[PDB]
Length: 101
Ligand SMILES: Nc1ccn([C@@H]2O[C@H](CO)[C@@H](O)[C@H]2O)c(=O)n1
Ligand SMILES: [Mg+2]
Image 1 (cartoon, protein in one colour):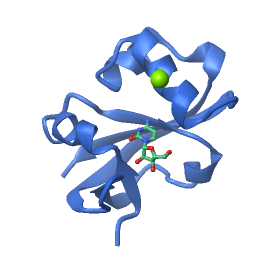
Image 2 (cartoon, rainbow, N blue to C red):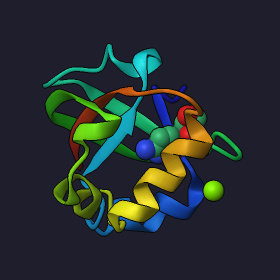
Image 3 (tube, protein in one colour):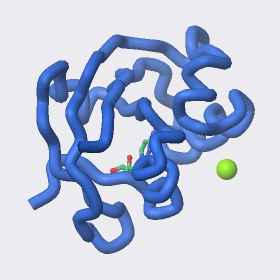
């Protein structure tokens, strides 16, 4: 079973180490530094890697930074657009920093 999923269009970015954080809402605020997590694709729940959580922090819509976007391998405009679709109306988020094992 997978502990967490990503949209499959992020799979290669994660395996290549271009994406090293993910921004989630309260439903995934329980992941914490030192967790070792099985990761699957959102679309088919297919496993593709195991990650280690290396850091966590809280962030809000109005405190997301260019650097958060860079670590998501996005522009900031791109990151805000994805959040507006995935977490409509939400402002409180949780940063999970990780590495692919
Ligand atoms: N920063 C983020 C936030 C969410 N997600 C994907 O969207 C699903 C629903 O939140 C999540 O389960 C996850 O698959 C993502 O890929 N990257
Ligand atoms: Mg959109």
